[PDB]
Image 1: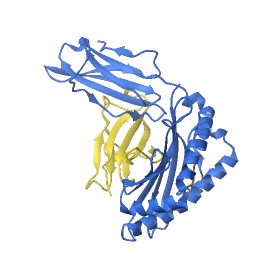
Image 2: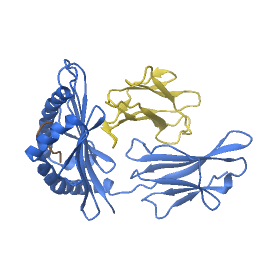
Image 3: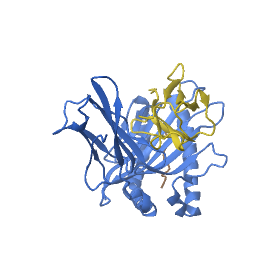
Length: 277
Length: 100
Length: 9
């Protein structure tokens, strides 16, 4: 079944005077976290955060640990440089973030490689989707852009994104196939909430599903349009699955005319649900 | 710089049944910068041994965390998530509603 | 597979 992604989300936060920056890296395959590194652990190592990763041997962990430690110093240095670029005080804490990885189609073609940075919550510099040129968000990032074009770093990153990023994603999907290539279908039900003599709320719940992509609709008899349905953002259950709900306000006594429709990869067809007195 | 304020959902892992064990979740997202203080509360009191996920972030660079604890809901006990962040001048408190 | 950054900022 379909596309996949390998992503790393790396955060470095300076702590001037309180010593070295906080450096945290987390890796995800699709909607599932699988590794971390945190500089503040008493013995900072790259570590598994999904049980299927315990299949990788000690050489993998040692190598990855070393890579994290090299970037820890990269960010130490780059944080000090950005402080100077922006003429900021030496004492304040600032944040650099970096996101990199690959999105692949089901035949493993690269749909998009990423290698991208933010500073203090705004875009700083990003490898463009051509994997050859750079987009600077401001004039401080223009100085970085020039240094990276001079260094030819784009080609180093492209070679990773087109090659190794994809090869390792494949490996992880194989190591974690029982969970990463599974679906868990939503368990769904409708709840009924009295309010006034004219109105009630019906809430359509979907629980325990993987992956996170889901769509809930409400229909009145035929369908639904120009609609004021309340929705929450899809949220983690904490056990590797997700939750979502969608609610409508309807006239008292007309509840049986409304149907909830749940759409998810794990179902053999959309699920239709009603309020069941 | 762009600072963003935390958006909060408080909810249980499973549908609540009074006297039956469950997990209480506080999902905090959409914030920047990443320093944040989150407590889960039972009738106003800080619950001990609350765990949280590893820090990560979304496409717009905003951070997110899941805070959680095992709990046993009852009819009368009130549960909440209390969040302090540099964007706020006093904590945000969101009560757990079992129907949301 | 974590990929180290090259040139600094």
